[PDB]
Image (tube, rainbow, N blue to C red; front, side):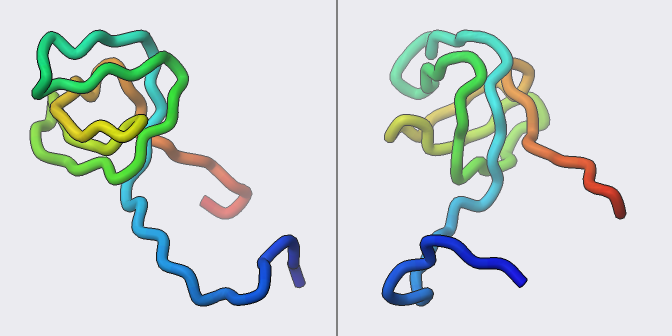
Length: 79
């Protein structure tokens, strides 16, 4: 049993998809690429290139190296 500040209704729509956390500060070489700070949170992460991805950060969707970021993941009791 759990609860919190649900609200007046629980019929919302949140499609964030995949998320990741930056490891180091990056500077999008150009417009195509996006610039995000280290230890930041990114949503709508689309897996395109094993080395580069595309997600919506601080209101910006562009190409970015998956090396300067880590795929969010937790390890609970029952893996």
